[PDB]
Length: 36
Length: 36
Ligand SMILES: [Zn+2]
Ligand SMILES: [Zn+2]
Image 1 (tube, each protein chain N blue to C red):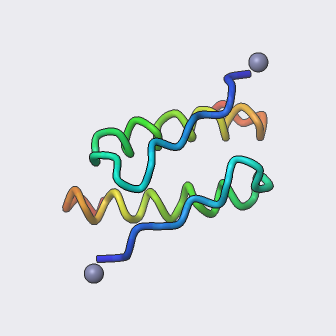
Image 2 (cartoon, rainbow over the protein chains, first blue to last red):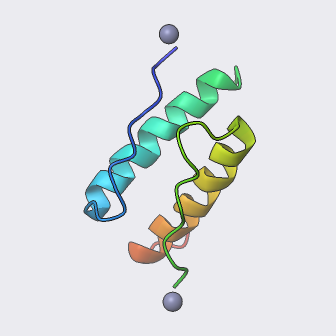
């Protein structure tokens, strides 16, 4: 599946923590085999 | 609102990245004033 996303830092702007959030969501669906 | 969650590490077990995911979700709803 997708490789594990890189955490952008505590001080990353909110738009970068929303991109990271969406990529962790993808990753977690794939690891748990639950692509809903 | 809630204080910014601590990232558990790249090597944290999947259940700990699902807890972090849920707490970042909370945090991001509050920062964006969109508590749906
Ligand atoms: Zn792969
Ligand atoms: Zn507060």
